[PDB]
Image (cartoon, rainbow, N blue to C red):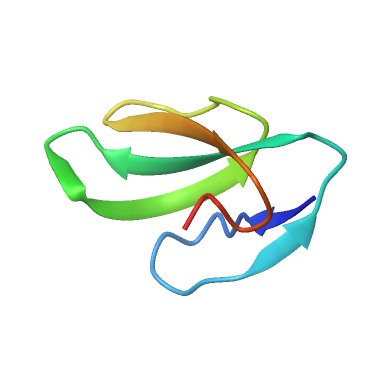
Length: 60
């Protein structure tokens, strides 16, 4: 599964992962800002909040 990652929540980059699912992370107060991304489903620190999906680069 190729999905987005990049810990630097400004530029963008993707990586391959085993997980069927991937997550996208936004600042809680700013839903309309998909800030960071990752594979599977949640991992984050406040004030970030995550949402999951499935499919290659679904976590746009």
